[PDB]
Length: 52
Length: 39
Image (cartoon, rainbow over all chains, first blue to last red; front, side):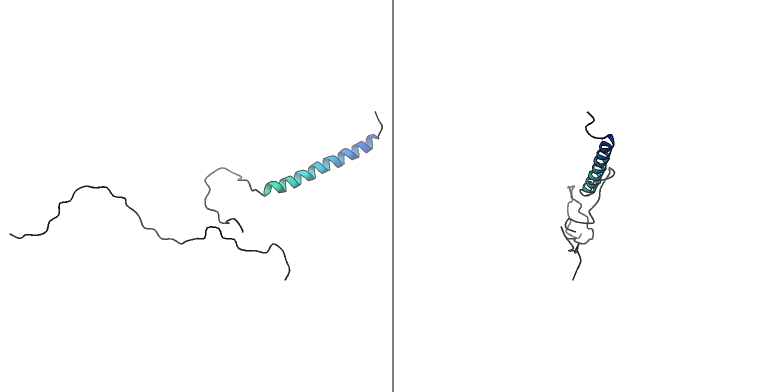
């Protein structure tokens, strides 16, 4: 109903997509911990035990 | 003739354990590294 400018909407939508990208960066850092095995195969011993 | 001790041997089953060298490592070792700085 055009109660706000179109440009103020474009600024709000840009801030919204920038913040979604910042949450994606924080989620990628939260996914690097709890480290995923990149491939599938036989795994050996753990050179780093838990606690190090 | 000589009389000597003679055994009568027969078949049986065995287990065949093999000896192999090595060291013992600790189960859960944690080197206390600081993660933060200062004296």
